Image (cartoon, rainbow, N blue to C red; front, side):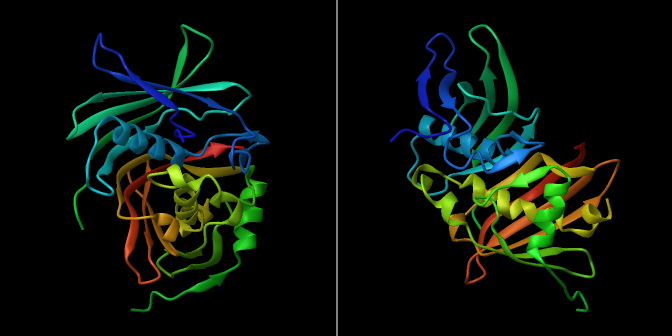
Length: 268
């Protein structure tokens, strides 16, 4: 009953830093279903889950979704090969804390893949659609080398505003369901929410694919797995493009909102 991504923790008495190691294998539940250029790469959303899971395991809190992620940098993609060991540290207090997520090659070597700053949760017109075919979006993304398996195909309905906002109908697929219990936030479900940015006009106007590299302000209010509508916008500023996405209830209540998703073109 231990967290399938985070694994088992131990606090280093020398410095109060907490440390978890975890065995990752491509054949792990629906990891196989997120691939890039024929390589299984762990989805960015996973780091968010790990960071939350790490905070929860460290500090007991009565609140249901007690954390928000101030920010999260996706410093390097992790190609999930057999017997990958994923190593998480956490420092800081129960108000604010830093997570860092690495993989370890043997002993004496680590590669940092993500860093997150977790904090306590803060509580809670002729823009009309061109209907779109989800199967098109997926086939396009397959063409740009991103192969979403069955578990990650949560976009069951899709459309774009004239303003270029992607509005999507999402259902967490069957294959993604199993193993679900242990997650503070379901990485597949979040990934799905995030895939809408790919349908945003800025993104489409851009082979090569656009991918998140940074999150800021990820808010969780419930079992996003219950989320059914996902709306993503993506503007281009500076040299850099940044979107928001928000995932909602059947009763239109926000389940997950990420205030900022910095994106970047990747050669494929």
